[PDB]
Amino acid sequence: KNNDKLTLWTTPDTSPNCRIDQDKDSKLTLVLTKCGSQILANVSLIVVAGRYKIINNNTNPALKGFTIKLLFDKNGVLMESSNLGKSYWNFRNQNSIMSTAYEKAIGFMPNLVAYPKPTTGSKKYARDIVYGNIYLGGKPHQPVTIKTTFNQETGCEYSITFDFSWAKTYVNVEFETTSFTFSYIAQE
Amino acid sequence: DKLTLWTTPDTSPNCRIDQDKDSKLTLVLTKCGSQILANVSLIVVAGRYKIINNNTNPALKGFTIKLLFDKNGVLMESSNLGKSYWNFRNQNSIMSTAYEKAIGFMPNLVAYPKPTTGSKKYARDIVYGNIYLGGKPHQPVTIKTTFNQETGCEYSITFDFSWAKTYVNVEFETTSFTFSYIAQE
Amino acid sequence: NKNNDKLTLWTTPDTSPNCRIDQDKDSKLTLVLTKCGSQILANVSLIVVAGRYKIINNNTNPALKGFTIKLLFDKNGVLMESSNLGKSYWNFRNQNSIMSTAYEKAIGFMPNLVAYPKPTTGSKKYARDIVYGNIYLGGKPHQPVTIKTTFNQETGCEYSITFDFSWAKTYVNVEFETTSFTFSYIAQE
């Protein structure tokens, strides 16, 4: 009706949907829009609770990054082992989601020939990585690196991994980010 | 082409930074369902921002171009960009008639809320990028894009241009930057 | 084939060399152009598999700081044989491969000539025909290379995409194989 099977997303709310350190400590806002052979991806992160909400590298000098993993089965269905919760990961309907959990999203999965699964004896190429920067609090001198890797997780058919890292000593800085856009080659 | 809202890609000035028609903002918004793919560049053709000289004007380090939209996604006259230049694509030009509705191109208000007393302002309504004056690799300028942070409108796209180098007799005409944002509908 | 995808012009996502930087088939340029109406969404990476740019050593070659890959197109948007990119696997998509026949027209994928004019002797050259990006050798965050993409600035063709790769660090025995970068450009039609 208003079902939008060309967008797979978290809904644009600020309600937590993600575990970095503890259940529901963060909102990963992730929008995957299918433009044929490419997925246009838009991502940001708000940490609402737990250890990563406020970075203080004076008190926690070793706290310099964390990972959010989306693991997908052979149908492109988000697995329970993901950091991202399944509840509100679905095809778009307006500002919400389709009324039923999707069964197939292979059109949204990172291409396995572009981005092969890890295997001994085959060369691992960097083209399964996209680097970006996002900025804590929108401040131009609070960069964090967002490294996105496709299909490098085990125990799944497809994966998107977000590795967040910083090299600056952030003192009482709320971990809530600007947005970044990237694309990747779709499986079909 | 009602999937593209743009300024035709010619060099004819369409924008007021400092004075009438001092610049060409080339802005292309392509609707890929729930996301708008945006491509932007700027040519300053006249007035105070045409040639940057930070020897003469050491405090001249940025400026803003605002697109303000009403509840129908129609560009408001208070915008820096002229309304007569902003329309759905027709070939290398624009539709001959004013659009009535472009809510599908507006930045999503739940993703990017209007400024409100008492409520948390999140940075996800910002995208940072760099563009390069004259295409020169050592003439970066920051283009900060903010969604729905202007007052007196339903929706907004704001381009804040800034630089942290002393540019001497540098023409303010930029490389292109691509970003996306979540659409209202 | 009703699996022909004339909204994707690409190299295929495989690792088979398709590009000459220094010598025949020394690299795989993975380039995917997806038509979203008036804009082409472009995704690019480079693997150098052989020849002088496979392993950078700026101790042995201190002046070696860049190279160029040119795609030159005729009036129909057909890739010219003189390009760095090889013609045989540059085609509209069919699944993970290409349409069975070489395309005759791809003007919808060409960089817009009003946005990005050809070089002319008397004419003001605007920088908006350039996009800058970074990619990272071996996926390592401290091995950046600049990828500068320029539209329609080559002579002897109707359209062009030029990739200028450069770096500003001393890379010692670093394999030139990159992360991916996404950009867009305004389409001719």
Image: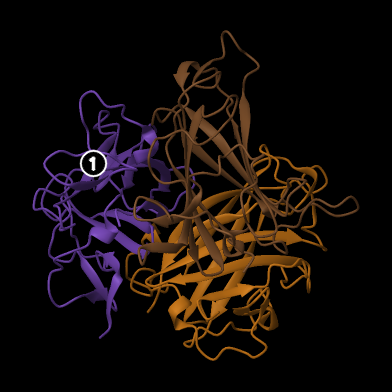
Chain colours: A purple, B orange, C brown
* B18 on left or right of A60: right
Q: Which residue is mark 1?
A: A67
In the picture, the quarter occupied by the C terminus of chain B is bottom left
Vertical comparison of A52 with B36: above or below: above
Does the rendering let one see residue B174?
no
Query: Outermost residue toward the left?
Result: A80
* B182 on left or right of C62: left
* B74 on left or right of B25: left
Query: Outermost residue toward the top?
Result: C60
Does the rendering let one see residue C12?
yes
Say which chain tag 1 marks.
A
In the picture, the quarter occupied by the N terminus of chain B is bottom right
Residue in front for this viewpoint, C74 or B156: C74
Image x and y of residue C101, in percent: 48, 55
Query: Outermost residue toward the front?
Result: C101
Residue in front for this viewpoint, B84 or B2: B2
Vertical comparison of C140 with B167: above or below: above
Q: Picture quarter containing residue A168?
A: top left
Vertical comparison of B65 with C145: above or below: below
Image x and y of residue B123, in percent: 39, 58
Image x and y of residue A89, in percent: 19, 64
The residue depicted at 39 percent of the width and 42 percent of the height is A130
Q: Picture quarter containing residue C139?
A: top left
The residue depicted at 49 percent of the width and 21 percent of the height is C50
Residue in front for this viewpoint, B130 or C92: C92
Q: Circle 1 sits in a helix, a strand or a loop, which is it?
A: strand
Please name the amino acid that badge 1 sits on: Thr
The residue depicted at 37 percent of the width and 40 percent of the height is C14
> Within 10 angstroms of label 1, few (less than 14), some, or many (20 or more) residues?
some
Image x and y of residue A41, in percent: 36, 57
The residue depicted at 53 percent of the width and 60 percent of the height is C40
